[PDB]
Amino acid sequence: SQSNRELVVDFLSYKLSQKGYSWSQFSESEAVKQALREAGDEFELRYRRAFSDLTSQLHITPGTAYQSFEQVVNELFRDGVNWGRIVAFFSFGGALCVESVDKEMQVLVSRIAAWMATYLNDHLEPWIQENGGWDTFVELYG
Amino acid sequence: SQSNRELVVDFLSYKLSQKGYSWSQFSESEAVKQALREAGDEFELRYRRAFSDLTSQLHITPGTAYQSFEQVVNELFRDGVNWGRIVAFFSFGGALCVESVDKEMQVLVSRIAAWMATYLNDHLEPWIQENGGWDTFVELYG
Ligand SMILES: *S(=O)(=O)c1cc(C(=O)O)ccc1-c1ccc(F)cc1
Ligand SMILES: *S(=O)(=O)c1cc(C(=O)O)ccc1-c1ccc(F)cc1
Ligand SMILES: [Br-]
């Protein structure tokens, strides 16, 4: 896609790495990526329980449709968009990739990356642009 | 206060009662009280980890100032006010009351109720009025 696609790929590469997997076998910009990597690790520590209940709701098979992903991701934004909720979303996507590689369905990695870039573009990009862009996120979270 | 104090007391009475403690031994409107009651239970269940990190932050001794409670509660509104964070606020106060009764400092329950009411008035009331009052919380969470 574009700059959102590039952000999704960086985050998923990091999440995969933390679990010992490489992206290569599946295929302010620096400050945005670093800040989002750090924000996702923090969110994963603080909301261990609630996050586990989220990831439980979706088990990605080669048959899962994007709409099934949207329905659970939509729960994160029920009451609107915010940075914490966008971080949760990245984290969520990262956990589905890890789960995918764990179950030897490494083909779903590029599929989740596409689903995420799409979801950011369609639903989150207007609120992001309206709230200072990714540079604001960095100034707030870096 | 007013509706806020009535809301605080109902919520605190409910929480204490759940653990087997009466409010009486220390001292649409129904749809709101009920909706908040249910929200507080669901919240306490969903954020097992995160809620525990917050309650840990303040251990109320009869010499704890309001400014102390306020500083830990500002942590709940760090990145803005939303219905969910207001629900976390009520749940937190409920925990500080159950904690006071259990730690033999059952006198504190009345002061917590007063701290909660003031916080709502000084900080939370404009956001509540701007987002359609408690009837909107009901018409969403109820
Ligand atoms: S949570 O209360 O932070 C929350 C709130 C919403 C909402 O729409 O109000 C959506 C999602 C979440 C959430 C936070 C943390 C998680 F691990 C999962 C969901
Ligand atoms: S979170 O636990 O970091 C958090 C963050 C904010 C914020 O404004 O950044 C507000 C509330 C919370 C929180 C949610 C749920 C809990 F049980 C405890 C804290
Ligand atoms: Br949690």
Image (cartoon, coloured by chain):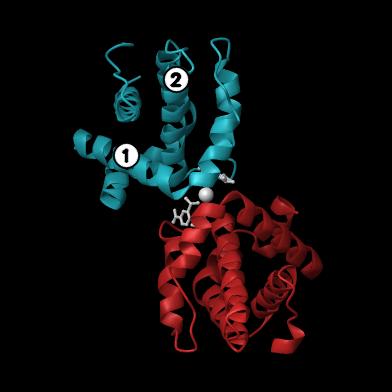
Chain colours: A red, B cyan
Residue A27 at x, y = what percent?
71, 89
Amino acid identity at mark 1 = Leu
Residue at the image position 44 percent from the left and 20 percent from the top: B102
Q: Dot 2: within a 10 Å radius of its alpha carbon, few (fewer than 14), some, or many (20 or more) residues?
A: few
- Corner quadrant of residue A72: bottom left
Residue A73 at x, y = what percent?
47, 69
| Upstream in sequence: badge 1 or badge 2 | 1
Amino acid identity at mark 2 = Asp
- Left or right side of B56 for A54: left
Q: Gap between marks 1 and 2, in whole Å?
A: 24 Å
* Residue A76 versus residue B50 in the image, above or below: below
Q: Which residue is mark 2?
A: B102
Q: Nearer the viewer, residue A70 or B128?
A: A70
- Corner quadrant of residue A7: bottom right
Viewport quadrant of the N terminus of chain B: top left
Is ligand 2 closer than 8 angstroms to the Cβ of mark 2? no
* Residue A11 versus residue B131 in the image, above or below: below
Residue B12 at x, y = what percent?
35, 26
Q: Is residue B83 visible?
A: no
Q: Which residue is mark 1?
A: B36
Residue at the image position 60 percent from the left and 67 percent from the top: A90
Same subunit: marks 1 and 2: yes
Q: Nearer the viewer, mark 1 or mark 2?
A: 2
Chain hosting mark 2: B
Chain hosting mark 1: B
Residue B103 at x, y = what percent?
49, 17
Residue at the image position 41 percent from the left and 60 percent from the top: A78
Is ligand 1 closer than 8 angstroms to the Cβ of mark 1? no
Q: Is residue A48 visible?
A: yes
